[PDB]
Image 1 (spheres, rainbow, N blue to C red):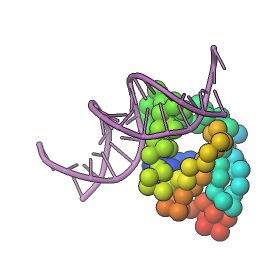
Image 2: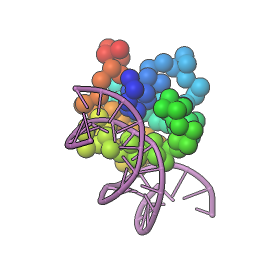
Image 3: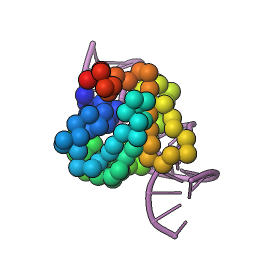
Length: 95
DNA sequence: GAGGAGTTTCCTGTTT
DNA sequence: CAAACAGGAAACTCCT
């Protein structure tokens, strides 16, 4: 999973390797939240070998996922996103 | 090389 | 006030 969204999912489905980076707000609906935004952006930059990655830019790539329905926009909830019908491998019976 | 997907950068404005 | 959220645009990195 070299794509941003897969990277996010991978962290969320591996809590035993999660430095309190993120957590499910509702695992059944695929609603999640960033607990350490810059820290996650850092790891993501790291993965692509880019020490200048920030949450700001990571979020821009996240917003591009709405049109593609890889993510469903969640309003009124800072740092809270939600997996869309086009994403996969995150359900309690899909992993 | 050409052209597209998926970001990465930048920026300006709005909202929380 | 300090972060997030919003998108349009343009530049980049792979892939076929």
